[PDB]
Image (cartoon, rainbow, N blue to C red; front, side):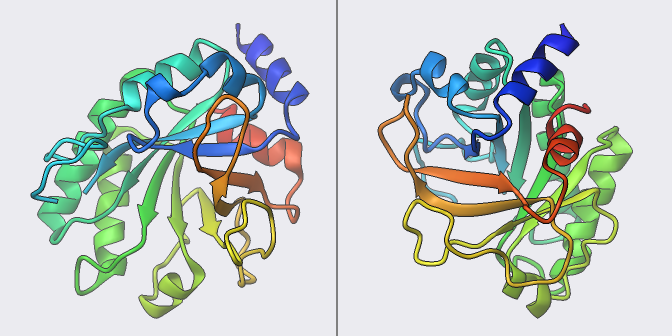
Length: 227
């Protein structure tokens, strides 16, 4: 039940939050082990490549998302989703948002995240908003933005209409927390390394933590326990 998931999450609150994509092969993940070593997970569903790869189809659909979502949800881990935002026009942005929503919504994800990291439209702020607005109109309520500080400032990426902000800052990228986002914007969650190692998986993992500037339990509830 819902109280059960919530109790497990309270119990595991100091375990890290991971994000995963098709680059992390489900067959290489011991989900039993991984689920007891994490508090939550954020799974890639879409990337916005004409060449073929192991992590997604040409239409942007991630090759592993059904596995990552189902295997973690069955183990009572709360799971949110993300899309790499890369439309070259409003039309592409709205298309990608629809593809993303339709693929992820069946799983009742705890949050939808826009992963914004390169300029694919002249006014990237407008394109990002196109994506966000479309997702909202399709029914997404929890819509957050992942964006680096320098990118956000360079392209005047407005985070105001999003319901949460997620920011990467790796320092040297050692696998450990070593530098926090260089902004006074009030973000909820910090991607601190791309080279984490967690029991249950042998290879590099993106690891995240709720910002120590927030109340940890309340912010975790916000991001993971309110779909």
